[PDB]
Amino acid sequence: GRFKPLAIKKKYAKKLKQNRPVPYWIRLRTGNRIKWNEKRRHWRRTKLHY
Amino acid sequence: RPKNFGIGHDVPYARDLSRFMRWPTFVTMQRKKRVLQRRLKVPPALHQFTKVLDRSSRNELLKLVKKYPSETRRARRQRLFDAPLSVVTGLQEVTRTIEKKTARLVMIANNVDPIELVLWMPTLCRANKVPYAIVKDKARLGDAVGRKTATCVAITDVNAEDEAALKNLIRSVNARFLARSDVIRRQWGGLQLSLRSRAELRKKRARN
Amino acid sequence: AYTRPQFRRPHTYRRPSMSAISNKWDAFRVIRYPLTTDKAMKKIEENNTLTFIVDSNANKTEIKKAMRKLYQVKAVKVNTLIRPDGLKKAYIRLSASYDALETANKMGL
Amino acid sequence: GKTVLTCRKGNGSIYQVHGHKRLGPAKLRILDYAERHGFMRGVVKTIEHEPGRGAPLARVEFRHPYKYRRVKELMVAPEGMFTGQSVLCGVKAPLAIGNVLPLGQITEGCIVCNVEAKVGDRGTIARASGDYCIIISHNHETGRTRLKLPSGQKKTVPSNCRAMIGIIAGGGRIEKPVLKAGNSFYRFRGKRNCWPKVRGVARNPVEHPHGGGNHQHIGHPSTVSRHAPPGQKVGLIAARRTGRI
Amino acid sequence: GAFMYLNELWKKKSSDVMRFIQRVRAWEFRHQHTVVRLRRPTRPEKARMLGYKTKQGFSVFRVRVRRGGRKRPVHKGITYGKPKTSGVLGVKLNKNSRAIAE
RNA sequence: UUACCGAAUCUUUGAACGCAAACGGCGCAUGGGAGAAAUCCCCGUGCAUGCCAUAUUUCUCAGUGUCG
RNA sequence: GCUCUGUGAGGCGAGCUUCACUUAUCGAAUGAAGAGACCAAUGGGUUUCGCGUAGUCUGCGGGCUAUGCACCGUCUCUGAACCAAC
RNA sequence: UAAAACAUAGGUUUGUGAUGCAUCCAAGUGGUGUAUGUCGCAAACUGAUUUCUGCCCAGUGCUCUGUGAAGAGGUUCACCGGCGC
Ligand SMILES: [Mg+2]
Ligand SMILES: [Mg+2]
Ligand SMILES: [Mg+2]
Ligand SMILES: [Mg+2]
Ligand SMILES: [Mg+2]
Ligand SMILES: [Mg+2]
Ligand SMILES: [Mg+2]
Ligand SMILES: [Mg+2]
Ligand SMILES: [Mg+2]
Ligand SMILES: [Mg+2]
Ligand SMILES: [Mg+2]
């Protein structure tokens, strides 16, 4: 609903902008290991219960 | 504009309540600590501090102590580039002067934080046959010596001008203690009734 | 002379008792970057209203004072919101005496 | 086993008195100097129902003895204590209904309520509705009147002890049958989580000493010893006799 | 040798004078907090044996301690496991009462 | 740029301590700031409790404690 | 049972209980809100601290027991209300 | 397993005058009934009303009525200290 302490909004805000595909250019670095983001989250699956 | 102060009329002007007030605990307790030890039966060893040198005699003696001050720190240093007669003061120094019997009068203070510090002292002067007197306050032996408290004072010696002034005091002093040493080692003290209970008994016997 | 059932402690006298720039907040910390979305471009021209991501801890009155200092223009109002992302977003509306368009383009926008 | 319900009421958790809507303690006025050397007139202001209590409580408003303020004060009402009545508490209070006057000054044989056992404790005996205690003797030589407690029970108390005059109001509550399980639901709504009372034989062997077994029966005498440890002291306690009388 | 007098005066704790002084204190101390700082020791000669010196930075405290044995804090007084380890009232704390006050 | 280390920087918190707290809340005092027809607004610092020391120009006091 | 636990007066028996006492302790009430006295002692002793009597004692200064003086000690069937007129 | 059980009102009985009764707590100037005060509280049994609850108190339960002596001493012997009825 509407209610959120801003501290919770800052955290969902945190996880929200953290919920992004890895940059394309990061995969092109030497010795790179990363491909997909292993910490992609989906609201319908993992829950950030705050 | 006179006011009735019957019950259920004009409110009273604020009368003193010191008597029924609830005091800070340290107040109630120093009051009760003083009550408690009048109305218990104190031992003769400890009661003797309740008995004490007559003040006209006391005032004479403390003026004598004041006549023989210990030298001040400013002067003691100044003397030592090369002591003036003064009263022995301090429980440790005064204890020697008794045992060595160099003391020729001693002035136990009446009150002491643990009376134990001095509780023995009257028996010790009585044994060395040193004249001694109990006196009202360690604060007065205090100022007499320039200290803020003195558990004891010892007139070990005096200039010739004050020889007799000491002697009459020594016999006005051991007249009350050392002479009464047989009496003093006997009087159990305390057991005073409250005068709220003395009067109650004054009247119960009044009614019978 | 006590006149309370209980004692109360007396008034006693009581004796009265490195960054070169201590104020880390600043016009330049408050306002950050103008926003260039097309909801905001609707406001610069249609509402005389600059949009800014602005420091999230800044408040409205500080955002006015910051526009006054950074862009030299009065803000008739500044209703901020903090974005779902966590950035704060001010829609500052300029006084009519100040164009929001002449100023935004002066701003490199 | 497992903790008996008699023992759990002592935790006083769920089992505490309700009393949110209770008006506060229903006591006599503080034993002022005025009580001890005169009287205080307070007018009854309003007779309240304290929920969970049978007797109405009165709201006598005494003027404060020592300061300019008026001191409303709450005590369980004697019957016939109408609002606007002027109560008179104090040693030389007139002897009338609602007046609170020293017990040794109340006439022998007259009935009193809200009596205080210890002097100055502000009224502890005879407070339940309909209840009272006749004064059955004075002993002016030793200053201790006797009185008959609302239970057939004599007791000596100092005459300096206050008492109110008359029966406590609201008498006869108990005479009316409750009829409904729901009616007794509400008398205990304002009291405590006392009710309903499950029988211990209906309980399990873990729950109660009486519990368990096939036919539901106590297996041992229901008359427990006074020294029985808690959780055992159920059934009839230290009973001197059993049986209908 | 004032210590020698004040030390043996306290060796007579049972003497009626010392028994009286101690009486008034225990009365006096009951009406005080479990810890109480003193500007001076009740026993100057005894405190000084133990290293107290009337100096700045030395302070004395009178710490009260209830007497009698420990009651082991098991619930409802019940004890589980072996019968040896039962016993609530009679097992004693294996710690000194000067220790507990210190 | 790397490596190291002295100078600093070190946001909100946290023992967390000015008071709170699913509140990015609210103080009092101190100085600053912007500003403005002062009010508002931001900022810095102090402000928890306990205890020890001290009042160094020796703080203010309380006690039907002891005396004088 | 001991202890907490003191104090006086008894009696009994070879420290036991009655009886009062009150400072421990306990309970109660209270916002610790008015206790006792002045009405006077088988009471007190530092501004009252002191005298006088008999008995005894003396560190010759006084003590102590009894005792009486003094002195401590002395005054009289719902109203409103405060913020004082030595 | 929704009953026939539990509850229930009604009935009785027990404790109990606050120094209380029941009762929580390791512990306390701690806690619950109790903001209460016998028309109350705590404990039990029975189970509306109408009607009746006979006989048995034997059992069981409940209730009620340190000081001497010996010894060198450790010690030992002796005397006083809730039950039974
Ligand atoms: Mg789901
Ligand atoms: Mg949420
Ligand atoms: Mg908003
Ligand atoms: Mg069952
Ligand atoms: Mg069982
Ligand atoms: Mg059945
Ligand atoms: Mg059955
Ligand atoms: Mg904080
Ligand atoms: Mg049934
Ligand atoms: Mg029936
Ligand atoms: Mg039958």
Image (spheres, coloured by chain):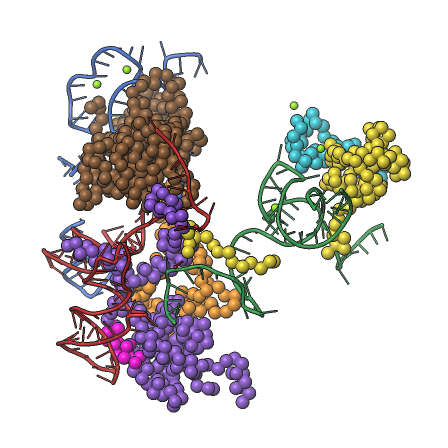
Chain colours: A cyan, B purple, C yellow, D brown, E orange, F green, G red, H blue
Within the image, what quadrant is residue B135 found in? bottom left
Q: Residue at x 27, y 36 (%)?
A: D94
Within the image, what quadrant is residue D176 found in? top left
Q: Position of residue E76 (x, y in %)?
A: 39, 39
Q: Decide if residue C34 is in sight here.
A: yes
Where is B167 relative to F22, above or below? below
Q: Residue at x 30, y 62 (%)?
A: B38
Where is B173 relative to E58, above or below? below
Q: Nearer the viewer, residue F41 or A50?
A: F41
Quadrant showing the C terminus of chain B:
bottom left
Within the image, what quadrant is residue B184 found in? bottom left
Q: Position of residue C24 (x, y in %)?
A: 75, 48
Q: Position of residue E97 (x, y in %)?
A: 41, 56
Q: Is residue A34 left or right of residue D50?
A: right
Q: Position of residue H29 (x, y in %)?
A: 38, 46
Where is G25 relative to D133, above or below? below
Q: Nearer the viewer, residue C78 or D226?
A: C78
On whether residue B173 falls in the magenta region, the answer is yes
Q: Residue at x 45, y 81 (%)?
A: B69
Which segment did they paint magenta?
B172-185
Q: Decide if residue A18 is in sight here.
A: no
State how many labels appear: 0
Q: Residue at x 42, y 83 (%)?
A: B67
On whether residue B110 falls in the magenta region, the answer is no
Q: Nearer the viewer, residue C39 or D98?
A: D98
